[PDB]
Length: 119
Ligand SMILES: [Mn+2]
Image (tube, rainbow, N blue to C red; front, side):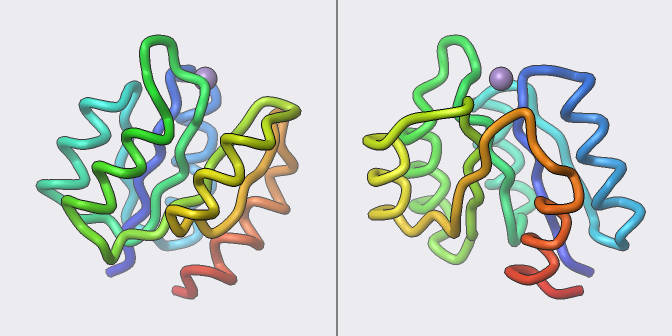
């Protein structure tokens, strides 16, 4: 039973992604901000997190940090705006697997997670 947590403030996109990986066979979870995200990491200890780095009021790099502390075994793929070098460098230093810019290529994300989190 492999777990993926999808963190994104936009319901449309979040639900979209959740279904993509649910159809793939993964056990999925959803969060709209960092606090819920942190909550689920704690109670569910998901294997992989798709982290939207642009959520109002949320410091992306910080939630990454916290997630790593709560569970240093969790791997993360960050989702950015079509940009940011410092953010990427910081997430790389923290162990982030890779990053994808929005709007994203569904097939690309899909292939990426099956590669980093085979079923
Ligand atoms: Mn967002």
